Image (tube, rainbow, N blue to C red; front, side, top):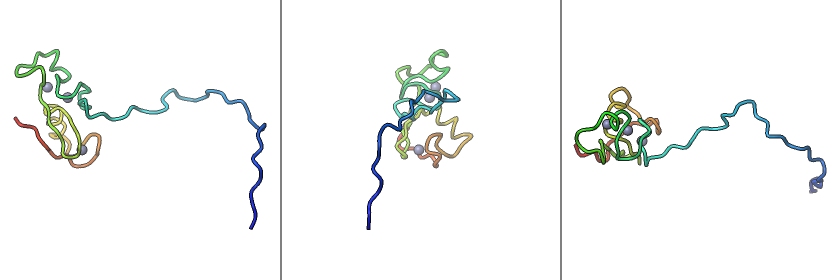
Length: 100
Ligand SMILES: [Zn+2]
Ligand SMILES: [Zn+2]
Ligand SMILES: [Zn+2]
């Protein structure tokens, strides 16, 4: 057998914060808010806060997903109306608990 070469320092070139585009990455997905409207969990939705929801303003509508997801029931219902899969998981959405 044998060994490798000895890593020598001093061959360092000065690095520059240099990127073609400022969009290095996106932001992580959160279930403590409704990603669909991008409003806080179990609270008022997009328009709904401006709209003046007439039921509960504490919570417009919320539903939990078996897939460890949390969205607004309103938002997820519209989503499901057009899509069969989670906006985040890209897996078929399943209702854990929604209530009404
Ligand atoms: Zn929502
Ligand atoms: Zn709503
Ligand atoms: Zn899911």
